[PDB]
Length: 28
Length: 113
Length: 6
Ligand SMILES: [Zn+2]
Image (cartoon, rainbow over all chains, first blue to last red):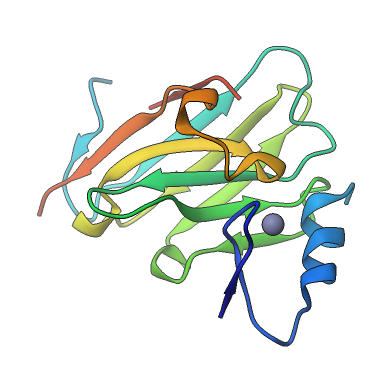
């Protein structure tokens, strides 16, 4: 399971890194 | 109101507040430094407040919330376990990796059983 | 962020 280097949130392979960046590191 | 020393089953509520409106437009997260481990993201909340993350260990028990008007973020901690013992911090998710030094001060929570 | 209480 992948940890994010910025927030240390774990995501599974059924949600991509670029989706993490949009949802959790942009403006909701 | 005295300190963070409590016993299991007890509940506590943490707040993190800053001057101005800095937390607005940023997702916020509660972090903890338990003895032995590195940072753990315990809970997070998107910028709008529409979405929410919880670490497995605390899911069901902890609750995160934000009030951009007061520039304040909250973590309601029910049913504390001894494994919840740590220093707690809040930060911008864009800053979760920065040195503890550049973060705020942090509060101990110390659970007993 | 700065201070955390309680
Ligand atoms: Zn992230």
